[PDB]
Length: 105
RNA sequence: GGUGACCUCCCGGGAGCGGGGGACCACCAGGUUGCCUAAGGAGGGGUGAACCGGCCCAGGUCGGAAACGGAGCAGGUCAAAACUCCCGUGCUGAUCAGUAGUU
Image 1 (cartoon, rainbow, N blue to C red):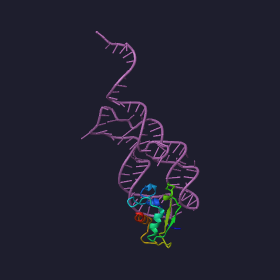
Image 2 (cartoon, protein in one colour; image 1 turned 120 degrees about the vertical axis):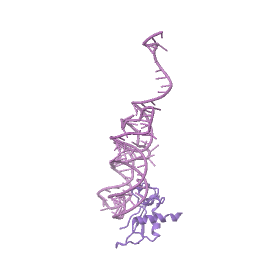
Image 3 (cartoon, rainbow, N blue to C red; image 1 turned 90 degrees about the horizontal axis):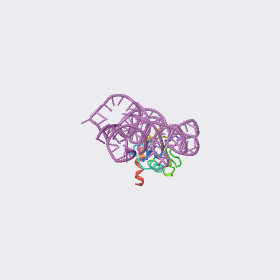
Image 4 (cartoon, chains in turn red, yellow; image 1 turned 180 degrees about the horizontal axis):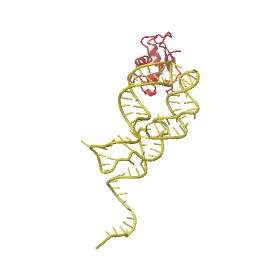
């Protein structure tokens, strides 16, 4: 239950910083989905679980392609980093951003 | 000096979110002014909706165990998106009396 949250808004290049986004547009992507996010995180060997029915507070678009939240574990609950490659939320996001595009395209 | 946006960094957080460094843009107030006008007030208003302003936001809604918060509707509201009318100012058609002043 002590896992960092991650909304797809954080990575969406068609959203302003005030609309949620957490990473520079240059590194961001178009319309990332919680599904896409979970898949690229898990596939690197991260412990991730997907909450299909959480919405972003700042998200306004009531249709399914923008719903969703991805929870990720960084820590084994002895305080140590599950992985050394992923110390921070930002380190997660930037990676997901880097990996999502190799899927569909 | 102010407002609103937008971009890019840190920092704290399980969320909504919290702390802080830069960059840029728009507008505002009112303090000096000009290689400035034919004349250019630092006026007065109104719209600000079907989503585009900003603010306050019932409900609802998203996040939350909750506190509370986000986004924001109906309604209210504006020194400060944008739009627009009026006043002033400048040129510029025109009207009336057959009015004069003087023939």
